[PDB]
Image 1 (cartoon, one colour):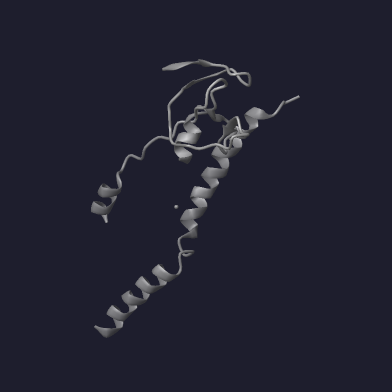
Image 2 (cartoon, chains in turn cyan, blue, orange):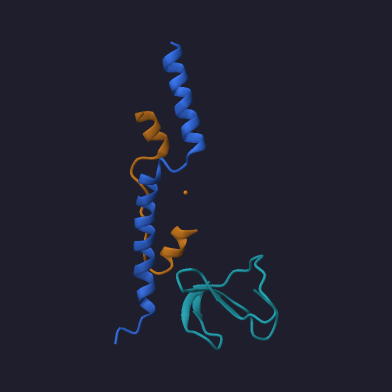
Length: 48
Length: 48
Length: 28
């Protein structure tokens, strides 16, 4: 669903979808070359 | 007959070995890529 | 030589070409 998502770092619009991407355990947020956030880790649990 | 067929073989060899002969078209992709990237990256600037 | 979807996230829409690669080859 397309909803407003804020986890501690930003307020924006997007659709959350599970994927096979893998992030380092010490990494939280990430962006593409266009300087827009395409992924956010779940704060409480482990999810990408 | 041997002059034309061998010349076309040279075009096939020059096109397969040298990929920079089409750089005139690759410049078009580069000019659009630099233009699309510059426009979206200016959104992060403070603009005074 | 995606970058198309990356530009569509900021509001930049990439329009598809009018003539498909199949039709262009049929022109050639």
